Length: 131
Length: 129
Image (tube, rainbow over all chains, first blue to last red; front, side, top):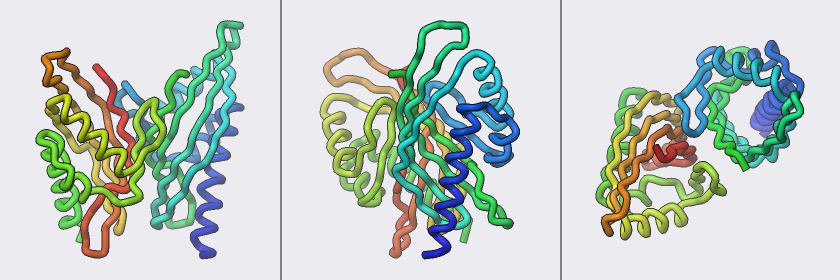
């Protein structure tokens, strides 16, 4: 039990840090939370990796303010991997003064634990769509 | 072993596709855990009976051609995760508009004690094209 609980705590820690480093953009923190081989999937787009994700986040932050609220639905550990499900609601506010946009939907993630006990995002499927 | 497990997974994927091209409820049911959760864009998570019912109803209405390319298979027993690229062609039996969909699915499989690899969690991001 203790082991599972500690792993769940560490994974939730990654998820919360990820959210904070998106609301207030922090490239260095985000980069540290994902594996070098990370793959992201979103609907209507080809899979993309770490540098693509970070570049987009950075550019996006130049243009918009992001608010994000998560409702966590599950974490399952099968060490040294884990899989999660989360519901996300996102509000995007253009810095220019343009119209506010909202998106929502579920995201499924796979995390990997290193030999040093470090949990990181390895694979993500994000089904957030405009609402 | 790892190799046997990867083969078993590709086999499940092939059987799943075959049981969609020519609908077979029993084959599909046997390839999912009872607690399976499916995610698709714009829809609430749904489970095993919901998936089977939808497939069955779909099959009354349309013919499905499906194609898949496996991009990744990783085994961490008793789990595995995969990424696949899919193309689907939908042909209404009524002669209505043929449709195409494409995109990716990320899947998590669990090995049962009898050693059956079954789909446990799926995110299917296929969209109309």
